[PDB]
Image: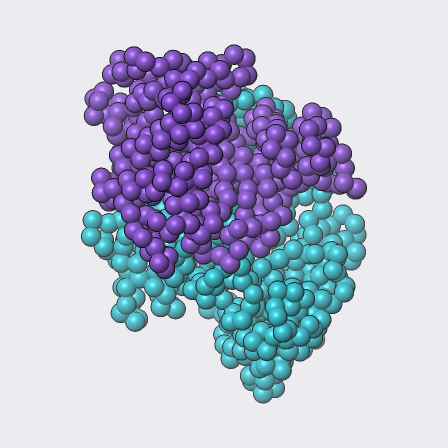
Chain colours: A purple, B cyan
C-alpha cells in the first residue's frame, strides 16, 4: 500500500520444501534505522556487482523496499512501527534482508527484531562465525574458531511473558504460585517482577533437527547442545534430553561407549558426527580455551544470544557478523549489530555484517557463485588492509575507507 | 553429632554487623568431593603457614570438619546429602570454607552449592578476577582485567521453580497462564516445561547496596549493572532501574549530564564512582575488547554465573578463581571449580582456587596480613614457573609440581 512492487521481477516460490528462484526474483529489503541508511546502500551495490559478475547479466535482483521501525512511522504515520503488510510481504516473497532496527521506549513496544522472528515463526537463528584472516582480534588464536550457531528463536524467557512488580497481574500469578502451586521458594513475594520461561519438545526437536541436518549437509564434525540443565532441569535439561533423543530416534545415533555422547553417520560422506553436550557456563570458557573442539552449536534463545555475541567478539567480527532467521515458509537475513545513531549518515561504519548476511541470502537462494564472489571480495579487502575505521584503529598499516568505499573494495577484490 | 568441635578454639561472634574474631577461632571446613580430598589439605597447610608467619604464633585456626555431599553420606548414611546441622554450624560459627561438591542425579536432588546459598541466605556471590602475572592466557592482554563480580544469589531462574513437560503441575500452570492470564505467546503449550524467573526490589537493592559499598570501601572506579532488560523488562530491567534508584536515593547519585549514568562521590577519597549499565550480551563482548573500562560488576544470578566463568577463562584462572557467598549472618568461601573425579586422589590438580578463597576468608575475618602473605606466595610460585600440570602444559620452561608441592611453593614464596 505504500510499497511499490517492481514492474520487472518475479516472486520466489516454495514448491514444497524447495525454493524455486526466478532469474529476476523480487527481494524485499528493510533499509533499517540509524546506520542502516549507510550500510544498506553498500550491500545493494555489492550484491548487484556479485550477481552481475557471476551470471554475466542473466540474473538480476529486483529490490523492493518494505518498512519497519522508525522509517515505518515516517511513511505510515507516527504510531505504526511494524505494519501488518511487512509480515505478509516477507511471507509472500519468501526471502528478505534487513538493516538494524530501533525499538522505541515509552510506548510499551517489545523489541522489533524479536517480534519479526516470532510473528513469522522464523524458529532458527543461524549465526556462522569464522575468522577472516587479517582482522584484529583480542585473542591469540582467532583462526581456531569456526562455528555455526543454531539458536532457537521462538521460545525461552525471550518470548516476553512477564509481569511488573506490584501489578495486579504479577500479584495474581504470585498468589497462584504460592497458594495453588505451593511454591515456597520466591525469597521476596512483594515488589516482585515475574518472567516465564517455556521449553517444549516440538520447539527443541525442530531446532535440533535443523542443526544435525546442517551438519550432514556440510559434513561438519559435531553438534554440541549447550544448555544450563544442571540448574534448569525442566527447560534447559529438557532441551538436552529431547536433542539426544531426536538424534537417536531420527538419525540413528549410537553411544560412544558408556555415553552420553552419540555418533551419527553422515549418510553421504560416511563420516561420524559426534552429538555431545556441555553446560553453558563451562562452554563460555571452552570457546576461549579449546575452540577447535567445537563446530555446530544448538542452543536455546538466551544462550544462543550470548554465545554468538561472545564468539563474534573473539574473532574481531562484532561489525561483520552475519545472521539469518529461518522458518519453514520464509527467511529473514539481517545485520546483527545495532543502529549506532551517532554515526548515522556519516558513511563510516562497517557494512560487513549486512553484506555477509547477503552472502547467506544468495547462498540460501542457490546463487552460490554470487555468494562466493562476496566472501572472496571480503577476504581480499581485509587482507589488503583497505578498511573501515573500526578495523583501522586497531591495525597498523591500514588504509581508511568510508563505508561506501569498503563496498567498492569488496567489488575490486571479487 | 558426628562433628567433633575442637577443644581449644573459640567461636567468632557477630556483635551487630561486626565480626569479633578470637585469636584461636574455630573455622568449619567442608573437605569437598572429588579433588577436594587433594586441594583442601593443601589449603589447610598454606593458611596455617600464613597465620603462623603473620602473627608469629599468637593466632591459630582451629579447623572443624563439617559434612556435605558425597562425604556426608559416608558419615551420616546413604540418604543425607545435606545434614541440617551443617546449616546450623555455618550459621553459628559465622565463617566457613568448602571444597567442590557432587550433586547426585537420579534422586530428585537440586544442586547442593545452590542449596547452601539459598538455605543460609548468602545473597552475595562475590567473585574477584584479576590477572596473576605470568599465568598462561588465551588473550593478548589479560593484565587489563581486574574486576569484582557481585552476583545476586537468592532469586532469578536459578531458584529452581519449575515443572516438567506433561506433568499435572506444568499442565496446571500452563492452563492458568493461557485461560486466567490470557498468555497467547507460548508457541507449544503441549509437552512444555515451565521455569519461573523472579526479581524483587528487596533482592536487587540489597545486592546493589553491597556492590556500591564495596566500591566506596576500596575506592574502585565504577559499578556496572549488567542486565538483559531490553528483552526482560520486568525482571532484568527492574534490576537496572532499582539499582540506579538505590544509587540516587541512598548514595546521592547524580546525572553525568542527560544521563543515564550517575556519579557517587566516595565519602572517604572524594573521588567519583560512575554507576553505569550495559546490556549483558554486549557486555560479554566488552570484557574482551575493552576490559579496562570495567571494574565492579553487579548482576543477577544467571548472568553473574556466566560473566564470572567467561572472565576467569580470559585471565587463565579457571582453576585459581576464588569465590565467596556472603549473607548478613554468615559467609561461605569456596573452590569455584568442579570435583574432577578422574584426577581425585592423584595429588595433581591446582589448589589455587580454594587457597585464594581462603585469602578472601582471612581478609573478611580482618586477618589482612596472613591474607597478604598468601597472595604474595601465589604471585611468587607462578612467577617462579613452579607450577601444577594445568599451567605447565601451556607454559614453556615450567617445573611441574604435584598439588601438595604447589602448596609448599606458595609457603616458600611467602
Between A370 and A220, the one lying in front of the other is A370
What residue is rendered at 29% in x and 12% in y? A7
Between A289 and A169, the one lying in front of the other is A289
Establish if B32 lies above or below A295.
below
* Number of numbered tags placed on the structure image: 0
What residue is rendered at 31% in x and 35% in y? A42
x, y percentage for residue B253? 26, 56
Between B132 and B27, the one lying in front of the other is B132
Horizontally, is A131 left or right of A250 in the view?
Answer: left
What residue is rendered at 73% in x and 64% in y? B37
Q: Where, by quadrant of the figure, is residue B381 drawn?
A: bottom right
x, y percentage for residue B122? 52, 55
x, y percentage for residue B88? 62, 58
What residue is rendered at 79% in x and 52% in y? B77
Establish if A373 lies above or below B11.
above
| Residue B372 in view of the camera | yes
Q: Quadrant of the N terminus of chain B?
A: bottom right
Establish if A348 lies above or below A219.
below
Residue placed furthest toward the front: A56
Q: Where, by quadrant of the figure, is residue B164 drawn?
A: top right
Horizontally, is B123 left or right of B248 in the view?
Answer: right
Residue placed furthest toward the bottom: B56
Establish if B169 lies above or below B39.
above
x, y percentage for residue B249? 28, 53
Q: Where, by quadrant of the figure, is residue A138 drawn?
A: bottom left
| Residue B160 in view of the camera | no
Amino acid at each position: 500500500s505504500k510499497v511499490v512492487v517492481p514492474a520487472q521481477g518475479k516472486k520466489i516460490t516454495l514448491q514444497n520444501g524447495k525454493l524455486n528462484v526466478p532469474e529476476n526474483p523480487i527481494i524485499p529489503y528493510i533499509e533499517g534505522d540509524g546506520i542502516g541508511v549507510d550500510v544498506t546502500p553498500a550491500m545493494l551495490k555489492v550484491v548487484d556487482a556479485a550477481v552481475e559478475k557471476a551470471y554475466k547479466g542473466e540474473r538480476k535482483i529486483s529490490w523492493m523496499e518494505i518498512y519497519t521501525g522508525e522509517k515505518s512511522t515516517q511513511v505510515y504515520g507516527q504510531d505504526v512501527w511494524l505494519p501488518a503488510e511487512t509480515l505478509d510481504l516477507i511471507r509472500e516473497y519468501r526471502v528478505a534482508i534487513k538493516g538494524p532496527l530501533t525499538t522505541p521506549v515509552g510506548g510499551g513496544i517489545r523489541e522489533l527484531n524479536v517480534a519479526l522472528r516470532q510473528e513469522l515463526d522464523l524458529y532458527i537463528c543461524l549465526r556462522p562465525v569464522r575468522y577472516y584472516q587479517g582482522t584484529p582480534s583480542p585473542v591469540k588464536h582467532p583462526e581456531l574458531t569456526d562455528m555455526v550457531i543454531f539458536r532457537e528463536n521462538s521460545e525461552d524467557i525471550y518470548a516476553g511473558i512477564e509481569w511488573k512488580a506490584d501489578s495486579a497481574d504479577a500479584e495474581k500469578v504470585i498468589k497462584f504460585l504460592r497458594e495453588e502451586m505451593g511454591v515456597k521458594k520466591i525469597r521476596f513475594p512483594e515488589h516482585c517482577g515475574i518472567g516465564i520461561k517455556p521449553c517444549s519438545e516440538e520447539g527443541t526437536k525442530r531446532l535440533v533437527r535443523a542443526a544435525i541436518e546442517y551438519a550432514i549437509a556440510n559434513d561438519r564434525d559435531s553438534v554440541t547442545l549447550v544448555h544450563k540443565g544442571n540448574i534448569m532441569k525442566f527447560t534447559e535439561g529438557a532441551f538436552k534430553d529431547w536433542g539426544y533423543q531426536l538424534a537417536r530416534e531420527e538419525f540413528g545415533g549410537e553411544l560412544i561407549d558408556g555415553g552420553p555422547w552419540l555418533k551419527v553417520k553422515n549418510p553421504n560422506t560416511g563420516k561420524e558426527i559426534v552429538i555431545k553436550d556441555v553446560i553453558a557456563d563451562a562452554f563460555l570458557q571452552q570457546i576461549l580455551l579449546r575452540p577447535a573442539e567445537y563446530d555446530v552449536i544448538a542452543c536455546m534463545n538466551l544462550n544462543g544470544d550470548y554465545i554468538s555475541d561472545a564468539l563474534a567478539a573473539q574473532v574481531g567480527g562484532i561489525g561483520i557478523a552475519p545472521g539469518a532467521n529461518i522458518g519453514d515458509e520464509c527467511a529473514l537475513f539481517e545485520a546483527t549489530h545495532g543502529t549506532a545513531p551517532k554515526y548515522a549518515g556519516q558513511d563510516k561504519v562497517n557494512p560487513g555484517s549486512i553484506i555477509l548476511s547477503a552472502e547467506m541470502m544468495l547462498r540460501h537462494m542457490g546463487w552460490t557463485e554470487a555468494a562466493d564472489l562476496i566472501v572472496k571480495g571480503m577476504e581480499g579487502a581485509i587482507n589488503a588492509k583497505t578498511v573501515t575505521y573500526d578495523f583501522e584503529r586497531l591495525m597498523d598499516g591500514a588504509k581508511l575507507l568510508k563505508c561506501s568505499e569498503f563496498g567498492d573494495a569488496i567489488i575490486e577484490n571479487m
